[PDB]
Length: 59
Length: 61
Image (cartoon, one colour):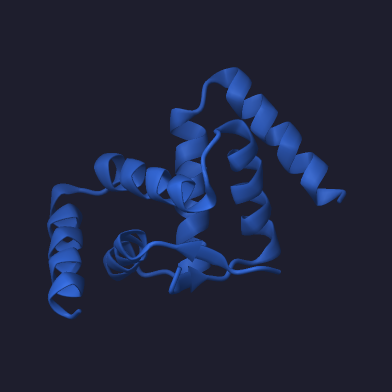
């Protein structure tokens, strides 16, 4: 429901990466989220992420 | 904050869940996952074009 507020340097980096790929803005956020979840969280961090995500979907 | 973005429900839910795993503000989390992707997933040619656009968005201010 609410917008997500960004600083101008962060908005600029999102717009620049938008140019590089060929995707809608929210689709880009999902790609980079997924990439971070898969390649940067520990095993236990990712299990808690999955858990939290399942809780939000029943909220 | 002048700038903002909208997200669909499913993407917003993934951003909120990752917020609960890290301990940073929304805009910081966005930056962290942007930078991680830029550094690790872009080829050298995409990265060059990313840096150029970033210089172009600076000029056009």
